[PDB]
Image: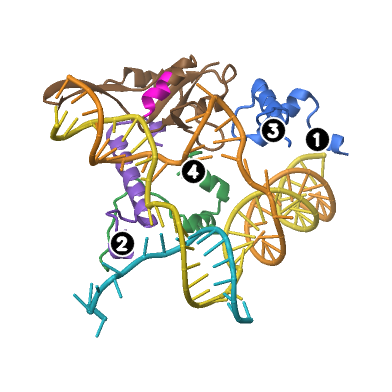
Chain colours: A green, B purple, C blue, D brown, E yellow, F orange, G cyan
Amino acid sequence: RERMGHIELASPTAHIWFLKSLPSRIGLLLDMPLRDIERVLYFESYVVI
Amino acid sequence: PPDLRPLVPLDGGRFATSDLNDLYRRVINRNNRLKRLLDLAAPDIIVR
Amino acid sequence: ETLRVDPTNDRLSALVEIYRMMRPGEPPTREAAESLFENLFFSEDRYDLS
Amino acid sequence: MQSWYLLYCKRGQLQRAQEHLERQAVNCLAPMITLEKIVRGKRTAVSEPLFPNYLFVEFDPEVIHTTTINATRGVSHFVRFGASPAIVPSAVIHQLSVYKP
DNA sequence: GGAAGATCGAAAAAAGCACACGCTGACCCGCGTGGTGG
DNA sequence: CCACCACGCGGGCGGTAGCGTGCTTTTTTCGATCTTCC
RNA sequence: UCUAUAUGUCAGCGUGU
């Protein structure tokens, strides 16, 4: 009832609570509109690092 | 932990699969297939 | 006023706009848009009034 | 002109989807790899489609609409990013054709 | 004379919709794919 | 050597498209304009 | 209290409000 497990994801995945719950935490931190955030997160447009 | 998402018997030999169990199974399957695709040297579009 | 507001000025443009409104994310094709408009209200199987 | 598109196919009906797509006269492609294993006591070189549940199609959207392909029996759904369906460049198909793992 | 901010109505998205108790049914993957052992 | 019995992973379903359709309040954003300036 | 008898939502309701 207490021991938990863990799954090693081969690729990083953003937490949906910090991304979709308005105001978006990632968008607020990066000061970018949510539209491009969901575009890059769901593989729609490249972003420069 | 499994006890928080148990598989209660249904008196007919079947098990009532919880929603969390199904979601975890789907996530595990997707992770396994993504690992297989990555290990297969697949192109960019498919892995994306 | 409605005639002034809308940007469409031909039957083909109106059909393309209707198809885009009905099925977003699909390539606008003239024959596909015509078929969709015909089936929306002028098809016996798709549209039926008792 | 004809373009290349990627489709997710349902598990098990990839073959019937391929026959249905060939029935509509469009170009199809899926990587092929043969592997040797023991079945029923005999060794056989059985073919297996690489990247399972994935199909590439060369077809012209004007002559045949995308929704018609999306509604074809045995095909799960078009692979798409955003509203518009994804476009596979010809170089990817070039590599895939010469891909011999 | 173009830009910036700004603002204002309009469009889109999220959350909530009282409590307690008693009863009935319907499960709680389907299906192409092995696979087996007659 | 072949017909009944497992079976094991994607899953929107089913199809060669379309399915929906009687609330209110709050919050966020967006297009169109505006309006005020340097 | 592990000593028995150790599934849940949905839909239809009904009762007290």
Which of labels 1 and 4 is toward the front?
1
Q: Are tags 1 and 4 found on a single chain?
A: no
Chief secondary structure of the magenta span?
Answer: helix
Indicate the amino acid at tag 4. Answer: Val
How far apart, in angstroms, are the residues tagged by discs 3 and 4?
41 Å
**Boundaries of the magenta span:** D13-19
Which residue is the site of mark 1?
C6
Residue B28, magenta (yes or no):
no
Instruction: Looking at the picture, tell me which residue is in the foreground, A39 or C44.
Output: C44
Up-down: is E16 above or below B32? below
- Pointer 3 chain: C
Residue D31 in the figure: left or right of residue C24: left
Which residue is the site of mark 2?
B6
How far apart, in angstroms, are the residues tagged by discs 4 and 2?
37 Å
Looking at the image, which residue is at 77% across and 24% down? C11
- Pointer 1 chain: C
Do the numbered discs 1 and 4 sit on residues whose CB atoms are within 8 Å?
Answer: no
Which residue is the site of mark 4?
A40
Q: Secondary structure at mark 4?
A: helix
Instruction: Looking at the picture, tell me which residue is in the foreground, D60 or D89.
Output: D60
Indicate the amino acid at tag 1. Answer: Asp
Which residue is the site of mark 3?
C47
Indicate the amino acid at tag 2. Answer: Pro
